[PDB]
């Protein structure tokens, strides 16, 4: 998932740069860009491959990490019971990150303080 | 039906197990049909040139010439089927080229149908 | 032409090669557009592996005893899981973007290219525990990462059943609850024990069977076929023989489209 | 003879390479249609 | 929670002992819901009085009575008396949602969670896992639904020849429509599944919430020795059955002797 996001971002950059050049060249002649002609056949293929990568019918996983012990996990058992499976219909999506957020980690490479700052609300119903 | 027809036309058969040959008969018959239908439905073009570029496209060429359709047929072998097997498979493929009984070798490798198709296409093509 | 997608199957001996030959033939009979790639252990004879070479496109060789094999270290930890670790090599087939794994004791009754519609680990609800996926037929997507994770699980926690089903069920626990599209209709992996154990449903939904899975100790190849009578050695009640067509359709396919290939290559 | 049977022989993969199914025989059938 | 109920069906005194155990187990795990048996005329007066000590409502259903809604259907399908009696669970329109549980089930933990699920949410059946074991099912009482079920009973009956058959035909959507309507098998653990595929009961048996004794020998039928809580089968874990017999002895025989027998 993270890799596909990277690919789409990289592709968008490649197409963006090519649009940049073509817009700059078009502007230099004194004409508003002819939108249809801006994108070359070469990119239409790159973008088509990119939109092919995106295609999925499977709901995104409820955890981010493959758990050495999955079935036992209290959080996962409860998520399944509660019915929050990140379904398209669901308005509430649960993402369980079982590792302390770290700069080294590939996904969300932000330390705890930065992640905390980003979230809108923090729920700590401590017993 | 298609395979049945091929036997009557070219006295050639394709084993059930081979996927590539089986696929080629489908492809070949469809291409022969397409071009024949095109010529019939359109105003007759005395010149239409069909360029077959491999052994498995050659089933079409065999049929086209056999159905006495007027389209010109070019058959191109980017590699010899028997050649690939005979090299490495035999000790001295290159010098004994003339000596080899092609039919025997082809049969021995259970590739005989494919060979027959390639040779048939070669004989069939005007060029 | 669909070079990107494959049916995979595992042969661990000549016995399960006859199974694979029948499965492969059945996929051809129902005109799959997808490549049938078997996986053969070193144990399959050279003569048999030529027959498997004719029917199946790529007999990729997986051996877990060779020290170069990716699973060899795992095998030394779990020496009882040789077969399982061999099967799990199905995930190494990164030349394919998506595959359907089918055990060599399955038989196809209709075109199932629509299995390729389903995503990773879409498998029939297993008879018995219906919260586990019969790993007889599962759509799946090759990946080195997934494969390595599976080996890790094999070493670390092993398998509850000491088999492919257990190692896969633990790793893909999400199947049971997450999505119904991952559940495949039972008709795509119809275990015969279902026809025997719960005959009434079979009577009603059996006609639509797309894949039959021969469970129990006595596999389809083990039976005796008298072509003159077209009747299999009839034991006392055997799950496979609850339906005298599913096994008959195994034996016929064998006789028609394999004994020819077998005799040619010296079996 | 064994004519239709010969298609079946090719179907199961066993062809008479040396004899009846030799390309030369196939060539004669091909010969029916000229260049 | 006067609005919601566990229902169960007793067709005789034998299945009354089952219901008494089920009912007790629901109480032990502290349900907030009503307990509502349905009893055929066949249950003795003395046993109905025992049932009253456990169940909030003992509701009489007699399909042989010509006033009964299912009576005409019974005359068409005389083999489906039990099934048509069970289907009266849909007539209980005083309740907005119910969980039906066969009298040969036993509760191991609080399952008020079942009330979260909607109409015909039932555990996949061992054997055909495309049919819903009608041992435990969440449903919403409705006269319309009930009448449609009777119609199906008349017209096509049941492929199985039981309630499972007729419910499966009507609620065929279960197999494919929604995964929320698939109850975890833990909520209906047919012992046969533990026996057939024991490796799995070992890992996911601990979490069992309901055991369903589908077998030739019913839980009441089994022989019990109180001396060590021992029993003389698909009941691979005899633990579940021990928990049946104990619950019976502790919390029923008292309520049994008190009203007869």
Image: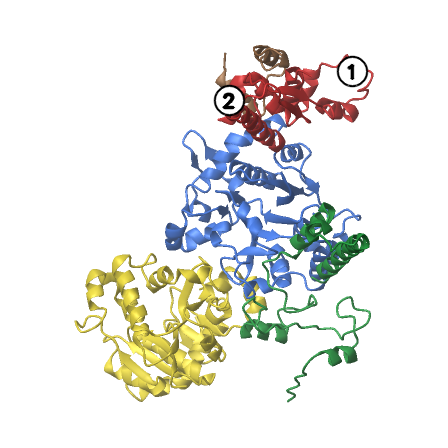
Chain colours: A green, B red, C blue, D brown, E yellow
Chain letter for the residue marked with disc 1 in the picture = B
Question: Residue placed at 49% from the left, 18% from the top?
Answer: D4
| Quadrant of the image occupied by residue B95 | top right
Name the image quarter holding the N terminus of chain A. Answer: bottom right
Q: Provide residue A119's location: percent of width, then percent of height.
A: 70, 79
**Could you classify mark 1 by the number of other residues whose Cα lies within 10 Å: few (under 14), some (14-19), or many (20 or more)?**
few
| Disc 2: which residue | B5
Q: Secondary structure at mark 1?
A: loop
Task: Decide which of A41, C132 is in the foreground and name it.
Answer: A41
Q: Provide residue C172's location: percent of width, then percent of height.
A: 62, 61
Task: Decide which of B55, A23 is in the foreground and name it.
Answer: A23
Question: Residue placed at 79% from the left, 26% from the top?
Answer: B88
Name the image quarter holding the C terminus of chain A. Answer: bottom right
Farthest front residue? A30
Chain letter for the residue marked with disc 2 in the picture = B
| Disc 1: which residue | B97
Q: Mark 1 vs mark 2: same chain?
A: yes
Q: Is residue C137 visible?
A: no
């Amino acid at each position: 998932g993270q890799a596909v996001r990277k690919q789409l971002w990289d592709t968008a950059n490649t197409v963006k740069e090519k649009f940049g050049r073509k817009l700059y060249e078009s502007l230099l002649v004194g004409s508003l860009p002819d939108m249809n002609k801006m994108l070359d056949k070469e990119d239409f293929t790159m973008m088509k491959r990119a939109i092919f990568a995106t295609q999925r019918q499977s709901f995104p996983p409820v955890c981010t990490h493959n758990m050495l012990d999955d079935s036992s996990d209290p959080i996962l058992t409860t998520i399944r019971r509660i019915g929050l499976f990140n379904s398209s219909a669901d308005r509430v999506k649960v993402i369980f990150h079982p590792e302390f957020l770290s700069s080294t980690s590939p996904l969300l490479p932000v330390d705890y303080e930065e992640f905390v700052r980003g979230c809108h609300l923090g729920v700590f119903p401590s017993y | 039906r298609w395979k049945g027809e091929l036997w009557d036309t070219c006295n050639i058969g394709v084993p059930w197990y081979d996927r590539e040959a089986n696929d080629a008969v489908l492809f070949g018959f469809l291409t022969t049909w397409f071009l024949g239908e095109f010529l019939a439905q359109s105003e007759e073009k005395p010149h239409v040139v069909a360029h077959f570029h491999e052994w498995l496209a050659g089933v079409g060429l065999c049929l086209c010439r056999a159905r006495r359709l007027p389209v010109a047929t070019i058959f191109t072998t980017h590699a010899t089927l028997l050649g690939r097997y005979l090299c490495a498979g035999a000790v001295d493929f290159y010098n004994n080229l003339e000596n080899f009984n092609v039919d025997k070798e082809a049969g021995e490798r259970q590739i005989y149908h494919r060979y027959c198709m390639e040779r048939a296409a070669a004989h069939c093509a005007h060029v | 032409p669909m070079t990107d997608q494959a049916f995979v199957t595992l042969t661990t001996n000549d016995a399960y090669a006859k199974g694979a030959l029948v499965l492969g033939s059945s996929l051809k009979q129902h005109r799959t557009t997808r490549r049938l790639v078997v996986l053969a252990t070193p144990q399959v004879s050279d003569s048999m592996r030529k027959v498997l070479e004719t029917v199946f496109d790529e007999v990729i060789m997986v051996d877990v005893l060779d020290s170069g094999d990716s699973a060899h270290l795992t095998l030394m930890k779990r020496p009882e899981l040789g077969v399982t670790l061999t099967k799990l090599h199905c995930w190494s087939l990164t030349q394919y973007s998506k595959c359907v794994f089918m055990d060599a004791d399955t038989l196809v009754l209709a075109n199932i290219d629509d299995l390729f519609d389903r995503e990773e680990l879409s498998a029939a609800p297993d008879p018995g525990w219906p919260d586990c996926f019969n790993s007889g037929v599962f759509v799946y997507q090759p990946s080195v990462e997934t494969y390595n994770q599976l080996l890790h699980l094999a070493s670390e926690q092993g398998s509850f059943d000491g088999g492919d089903q257990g190692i896969l069920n633990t790793f893909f626990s999400s199947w049971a609850t997450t999505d119904i599209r991952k559940h495949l209709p039972f008709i795509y992996n119809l275990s015969s024990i279902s026809i025997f154990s719960y005959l009434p449903a079979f009577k009603v939904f059996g006609a639509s069977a797309k894949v039959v899975h021969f469970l129990g100790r006595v596999k389809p190849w083990n039976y005796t076929y008298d072509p003159k009578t077209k009747s299999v050695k009839s034991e006392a009640h055997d799950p496979n023989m609850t339906h005298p067509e599913f096994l008959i359709l195994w034996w016929n396919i064998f006789t028609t489209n394999v004994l020819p290939l077998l005799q040619q290559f010296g079996l | 003879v064994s004519s239709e049977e010969r298609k079946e022989r090719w179907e199961q993969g066993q062809a008479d390479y040396m004899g009846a199914d030799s390309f030369d025989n196939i060539k004669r059938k091909l010969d029916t249609y000229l260049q």
